[PDB]
Amino acid sequence: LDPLVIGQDHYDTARGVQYVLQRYKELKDIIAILGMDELSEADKLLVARARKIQRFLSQPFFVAEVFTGSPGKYVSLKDTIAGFKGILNGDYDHLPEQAFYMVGGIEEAVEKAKK
Amino acid sequence: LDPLVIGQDHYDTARGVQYVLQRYKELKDIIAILGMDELSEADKLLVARARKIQRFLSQPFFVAEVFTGSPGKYVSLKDTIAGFKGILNGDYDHLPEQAFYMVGGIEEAVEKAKKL
Amino acid sequence: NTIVVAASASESAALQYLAPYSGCTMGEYFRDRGEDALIVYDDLSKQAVAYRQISLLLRRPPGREAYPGDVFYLHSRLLERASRVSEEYVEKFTNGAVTGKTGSLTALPIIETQAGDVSAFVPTNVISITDGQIFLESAMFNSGIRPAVNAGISVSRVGGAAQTKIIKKLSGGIRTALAQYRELAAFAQFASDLDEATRKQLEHGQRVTELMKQKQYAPM
Amino acid sequence: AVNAGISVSRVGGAAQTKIIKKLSGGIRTALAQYRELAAFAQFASDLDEATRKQLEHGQRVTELMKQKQYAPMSIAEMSLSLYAAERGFLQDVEIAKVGSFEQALISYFQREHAALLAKINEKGDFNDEIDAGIKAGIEKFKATQ
Amino acid sequence: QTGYKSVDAMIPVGRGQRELIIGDRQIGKTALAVDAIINQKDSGIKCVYVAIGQKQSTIANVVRKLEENGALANTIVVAASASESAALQYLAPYSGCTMGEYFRDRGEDALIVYDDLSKQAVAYRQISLLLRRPPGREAYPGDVFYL
Amino acid sequence: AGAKEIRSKIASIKSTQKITNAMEKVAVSKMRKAQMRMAAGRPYAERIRQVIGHLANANPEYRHPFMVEREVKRVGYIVVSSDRGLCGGLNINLFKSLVKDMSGYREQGAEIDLCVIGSKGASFFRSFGGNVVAAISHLGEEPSINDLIGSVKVMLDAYLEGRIDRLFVVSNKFVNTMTQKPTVEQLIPLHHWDYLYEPDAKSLLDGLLVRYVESQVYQAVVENNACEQAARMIAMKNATDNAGELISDLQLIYNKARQAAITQEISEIVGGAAAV
Amino acid sequence: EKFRDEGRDVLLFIDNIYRYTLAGTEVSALLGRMPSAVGYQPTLAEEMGVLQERITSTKKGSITSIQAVYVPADDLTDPSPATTFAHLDATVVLSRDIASLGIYPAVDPLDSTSRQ
Amino acid sequence: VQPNMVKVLADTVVRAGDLDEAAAQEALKAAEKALQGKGAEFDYSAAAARLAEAAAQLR
Ligand SMILES: Nc1ncnc2c1ncn2[C@@H]1O[C@H](COP(=O)(O)OP(=O)(O)OP(=O)(O)O)[C@@H](O)[C@H]1O
């Protein structure tokens, strides 16, 4: 994870994902005591994008087909960079967060949102 | 720190400073969670006087001018007792908290407040 | 009226370990002849440190916080001597010279804790040995209450049997007012919105708590 | 008292019989929808239809898994209770009368359809004949008992 | 089959599986294991119940509940109660395991309950500390996973 | 990790827990104060409504524009909201019922116009872009009816010129101390002896309908303030309970660290004593 | 045990079981045994079990025990109450708030438990 | 006036147009308009359903 190995785009997407998850980790006690309603508006937007990032990091596995019955997925690197960039830019702010859970691509989250 | 050694006035100034700081030690996390507006009026006045007490405890030193960049100060005992009594009595409730940081005597805090 | 026994910090650990027993023997002189005595041990914690030094240098096997297995026996042997003896013991000891009088030795041991940790080994032992504890707190000491007695957790097992009639009659409402102030102490900055009886209990608790302050060297 | 959130078997349905593996696919998800929504029953009258029906199914599956000590159930009786939970025959039955419902259903299948329960208790087989006989017995129980 | 609806529906146990039963005190661990033993009385699977560190009245109540439900004749009970030596408490699971391995090695099927492996580790900790072996986490020996 | 920082977090969440337990009782006292301000405005409005319902039947020769209805595609809404936080779903369920009633007119092609009371509704239509025709904030814990006169007159003047055809008010009603119900309530479309009239009774009707709309909006504002204090009571009780849950979890972590520290110190003492 | 072997039902009161445990810690420290977790003796469960397994109901008579329990540092997961609570069949909790109402005996009906 | 009941329904302030029109003008002027939205947006429910589901995790 170094810009002279993987390129600037993949590195910038990974640093933005880690920034959003770190600022979500710093708000855990104040969300547990007072709730999401007393945050500011950019904080509320970052908690919403952080829960969509946390749901989109999961993946069904081919060796975990016995545990669930859901089929496994192989995701290429280009689709992962494009999907996490589209979550970080705000392209999927209208999607619910449970559509981002246990899918392969971002397009499967788009088809799971219409169900 | 006895009233028969340093006098009554020095002892009441030191115990007043310690009482205001011990009160603000119990109010810090409350302002850190809900904010400043959710307290009563005497809590707001005591938190402002306490932050000014915590900045006025600081001092530039002659041997630390290689670390601060600012020259050092020598402050007498009576200047210290009069300045902390003037912050405790509310005679500087109008000055900002940054005016009392790294100054020396209470007159230097008044001169610094005109430059912010 | 006072015998002072000293085993200072530059003396031998054997003398620091033996000093409370030597002072207890001097106090017991008055208990065995139908008179009354009071002893203060200003640090039993340092006596345990000196006995730990003696036991570790003699290669005796260590335990919790490297204290030996007989440190509870060290403090229990000392603190069970403080007692009230009957008139029959005093008549047996003096061969009938002192008749119809009880004798006593009252102890006030002093334990220093580390940041309020009363569950360390030597404080747990002396708390379990004694008849009661007076806890002093640093936060009440910094808040202006100069006798820093936490009345919520301090306890005497003897209680109102060790009181005169006027003090035992007057002290119960002061105990009730301090317990009501400990329940209502958070409401003092928002007392303008309270109920009238709750405000009256809060003001009475504030007045009793302000009355519990007292200067040094002025006993009443 | 089984915490369904963190209990797991690594072998799973490779060990299970056929009717039990077929009818228990919807139990864990009904208990999963109940985990967080179990604290919402104090205000659940002002909720949408899918959240209300998921919470009602969660209370019914939670009341179905209660069981006394020293009362074992066979393959056929747990298959009857799991089919009564899974196929929507608990929907018009209140919570305090779930398990009594279960006991009465077991007794009815012991006196009317005993050859069906002896067919299920051989090796846990499932097919369309067993499916149709169970659903006809449960509909006759829900209509006449 | 344990005979419970939640266990046989959600967490199924097979022949040869190791399945842990874990939780706090007095919430039904002996109850689930004893009812799994009682459900084997007509299934062909023979049973071993090893009690480690338990009270004797608890063991006698367990064997009376095994006889009252008709499953004592299918079950070997191995007992090392709370006032026995720690050597017997350490060695009783391997003795009951050899008793189940007799039926394993001849093409038959057996089922064993170790009703506290946590008390066996406490007894092995006692034996290892009296041998002055150097301990690790929670004063347990270094080979406690191996135990 | 170590027990000192766990002990300091336990002291911090305990110092939060005491004052949230205090401000629940402050919300109880301000709810009872808003209830005695709720109880005083009713015998004005029932006497005004009885006089209006007598005068509309005794004189059919004049109809005011408020009393009759027009079926033209525009409606108006008066939204009553608070200015502070710590209300658990008062504003949010009110806003949910507001977009629920607004979507039936928005799909028809009708235009909508909004009057906003409170800072949170002003933040709502400032963030999402509602078209506001009148706004007011910073009304305190006792609101007065002379503050509401202007926004109510802008709402009524927009009715009188034919721009608004129907007016509603969206505010929370006090069902009990545990229940706040978000409603939408219509405002502008509302013994055989006769009152003598010292002026013309037409101008009497023209005055009394305007005073009735002002009394209904003021009763909705004071009842929404009591619902705000009841929601603040429920939210501080929930904050005290979740603080106690975090204190219990941190106390289990502290007791684990205390036992591990005693075991590590004894292992170091025994291993040091065995080498000498 | 002699009173049980005359055919009777005997009560046995133990004033503190934690002092029995601590006397075992002290005796094991005097003999030079290597200590176990949180400072205790390595024979902690065995020395508890030798005392508690003799308190039973037999075919001649029974001994029933009432033992007062101290909990160190208010920690129920400390090894001395965790070894003691494995042998207890009932708990009786005494309360100050029931005794301040004048109700005697001051047994809390919600905090007292029983396996029976 | 009723022959058994007198009801005076009073005023908190003097109702004249010079006091009431200035309040109407201050109510028109204080309407904060930051963006000229069309009113037909979807983003109300997209914030509101998330904030409605977030409130029940607290209680
Ligand atoms: N399914 C059940 N329904 C009702 N009561 C039950 C059930 N299972 C267990 N119990 C009761 O729960 C109590 C505790 O059960 P049990 O003795 O099995 O617990 P445990 O966790 O094994 O305890 P121990 O610490 O003694 O090993 C018993 O009194 C038992 O009767």
Image (tube, coloured by chain):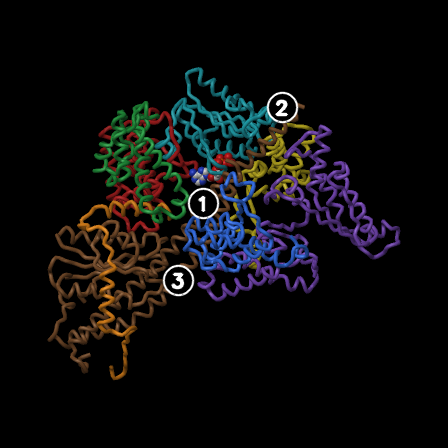
Chain colours: A green, B blue, C purple, D red, E cyan, F brown, G yellow, H orange
Q: How many marks?
A: 3
Give me the C-alpha separation between circle 1 and circle 3. 28 Å
Quadrant of res H54: top left
Q: Which residue is mark 1?
A: F245
Q: Left of C26 or right of it: where is A8?
A: left
- What amino acid does circle 2 point to? Arg
Element at badge 3? helix
Quadrant of the drawing holding the N terminus of chain E? top left
Between circles 3 and 2, the one closer to the viewer is: 3
- What amino acid does circle 1 point to? Glu
In the rendered structure, find residue E132 and report the number of the disc placed on it.
2
Q: Position of residue E7 (x, y in %)?
A: 38, 32
The chain under label 1 reads F
Task: Specify whether tag 1 is near ligand 1 (CB below 8 Å).
Answer: no
- What amino acid does circle 3 point to? Lys
The chain under label 3 reads F
In the rendered structure, find residue F30 and report the number of the disc placed on it.
3
Give me the C-alpha separation between circle 2 and circle 1. 42 Å
Give whichever of F6, F119 is nearer the camera: F119
Give whichever of F240, H33 is nearer the camera: H33
Picture layout, residue C211 above or below residue D138: below
For this orientation, the residue located farthest to the front is B71
Few, some or many C-alpha atoms within 10 Å of disc 2 (few <14, some 14-19, many ≥20)? few
Give me the C-alpha separation between circle 3 and circle 2. 69 Å
